[PDB]
Length: 258
Ligand SMILES: [Zn+2]
Image (cartoon, rainbow, N blue to C red; front, top):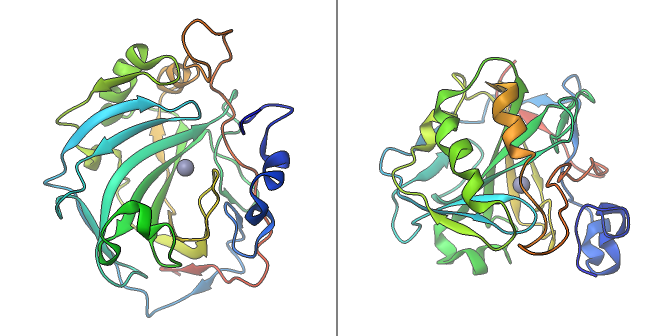
């Protein structure tokens, strides 16, 4: 009876195994654009992905992760609200069964069709497993996906999904450039939060980009053909793998832009 996104094990149940689900800095949240505070002290983001080395793509039973070599400062995030250097370890998406839902964060209650999370860890803690135990351990760049024109830089991901249809499958996935997934503008909101899946640790500085990327209906349809289940188990489509918005509590969302 593992956690998941179903009727009997979904987000409303997670607090029984993970009591931090009811904590003070849980994610995602609704971003109220009119009460977000413009902070002129916030620096521009510095995304240095030119030397990124992707390794593999994996269906882990709740999403698919594209994993990167994080043994050196090859793909790093700096600047913005961050102190120090954060190394990219993996990216994954959350998506819906329908185009009108799928994102985890919302903007003035608006849901997008999907949300991309680029997960980075603070190099001062030496490895990802130690970083998640620290309040400043991770930085997650969140990018919204809306349905419209196709995103050419996403197609290489879409075309490999047939190889990792079921939980536990992996495929080699080298030479993928994550720069093809970024919007034109790097304006952002930021707030302190958590992982949005168990163990729900409160270790994330969230950086949510204002500008969505567009993907085609055909691209997102292919996400919805993945399976939560392993091979030979009954088929359950991997859809609606998003956590609903959590209370903001004593937190202020800051904006890098007016
Ligand atoms: Zn995520």
